[PDB]
Amino acid sequence: AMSKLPENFLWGGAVAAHQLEGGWQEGGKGISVADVMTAGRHGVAREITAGVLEGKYYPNHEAIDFYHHYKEDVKLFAEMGFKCFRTSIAWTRIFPKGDEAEPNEAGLQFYDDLFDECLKYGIEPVVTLSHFELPYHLVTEYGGFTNRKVIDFFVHFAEVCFRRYKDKVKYWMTFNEINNQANYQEDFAPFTNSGIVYKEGDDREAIMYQAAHYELVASARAVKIGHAINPNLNIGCMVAMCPIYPATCNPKDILMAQKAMQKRYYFADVHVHGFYPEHIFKYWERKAIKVDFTERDKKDLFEGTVDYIGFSYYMSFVIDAHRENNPYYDYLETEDLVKNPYVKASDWDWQIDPQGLRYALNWFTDMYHLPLFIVENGFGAIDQVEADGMVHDDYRIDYLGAHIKEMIKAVDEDGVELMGYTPWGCIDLVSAGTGEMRKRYGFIYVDKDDEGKGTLKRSPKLSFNWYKEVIASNGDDI
Image (tube, rainbow, N blue to C red; front, side):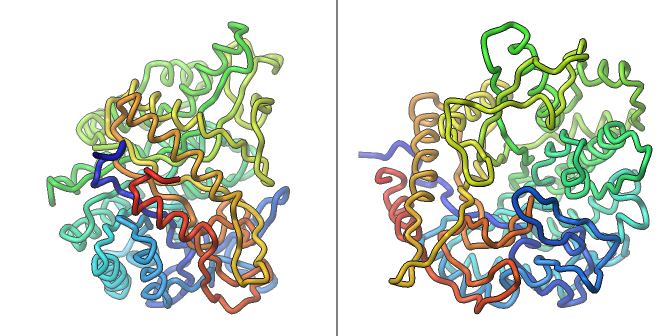
């Protein structure tokens, strides 16, 4: 009487350092890109300031103070019975500026301490190396990942981590949601993925492709050094998977969707196959995009392919061919997408499409034939604390449950290889897109609001014991 998922299935929860740690200057930690992004809300972008200003509010400076409370928080993960815990190693804790010859021992010791605590409860760390938090010094001094020299800085950082934690961390990924910057029309993705600050007159698209290239090379180099240090390390990529559906069976919509997925997911082709799709090269030729791309990069990419594909899944998109003056079927994430009339959406307009997770699992499997890891899934919503002192987040339970059902079908009916599942923001943390506390994801409520007020007390939500039971039954009872 076995369950539909494997016994060793990696149930857990996922966060990122800059979103929860706080202690932004503790232990000599340097200023990161997250440290110069002000709070926003749905409809208003976060302000990216030229540094830490006096009149501005930076929610990531303090976040939820996990840096100090992690022992208590990890205890809560263990109560739910996490098999793993996904977080990032704050680049700026190890290399405050990014270009130092030696790593920061206080920073390395903190993660030794964090990882040890997880392992005390049998929780396997899962580590993302870059998660929207590169050293701001790299942005100002080198222009972020628009500079080839930054590749080496990243690989040095990676090597240091691989060496330090080679016997503590089994599962690694290189660049969080590396493909977000396919949307180069807005400032968020290029800043957070790549430390790109645009000036007037910039060819935003060309710059993005150059930075993406350097990151793909850096990823490949990091895969090679990690495996050289310990061949048993599982090192994956991380892509934001938003399936793009054609609006209708009009052949033009069909081609738009195919070409859009090509543009949004070519990163995965490079991570997995070790070379660029020819359609990318043709596109660059057409747009007169020039990329510094050497024979050595070519070799590195081919030799540094990943062991597995980590991905986030929250929603699906729809595209059509309505946009005029688009004879080459270019993809603009901010203009070509339309709403799906067959689904509901969150209060932040994120479409709710659990079945799309099954499509995504199959798409990755059919294209790449690698094991997969759902390393983010979540429902960001306003929570209210009931009279009983608990959030009765049945809406969050319903969302997660619906996706778990589909992922189990993908394993059980479709045969996809799925390593595990870590819901995003398992403890309430500072949101990425908007920098909000009110957009809550957690099984654990944290008392901190968007004016920075609150005790920071942790309290289990209704979803807390729900998920505990999910894990205990290995998904048999949802």
